[PDB]
Length: 118
Image (tube, rainbow, N blue to C red; front, side):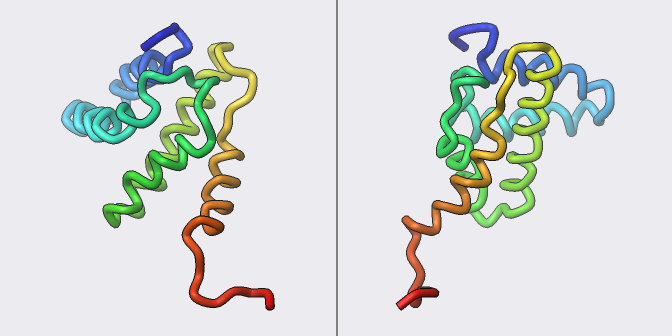
């Protein structure tokens, strides 16, 4: 965590806030799985300074294991934290739309077997 705008910092605030909504055991391990996969990717980065492909790399992390719901849940909670950062006045713009663009454009790296053009 470099600055106060670091993802982990804001995540903790949001986490401890949501901790009063979710079950304690659920909340703890929810953070645990988020920390386990997200932290190596974008955890120590600034929420405003996160690369579009890095957020997609988080989704990549879960999707490649087959965890489709969890990959989408990552995107969900990340965007949820992005939202929280906008509310607290840390970020004005969040690369949430960029996540979608990166996920879409990623099919230009993972090629098909036949294309839609000739």
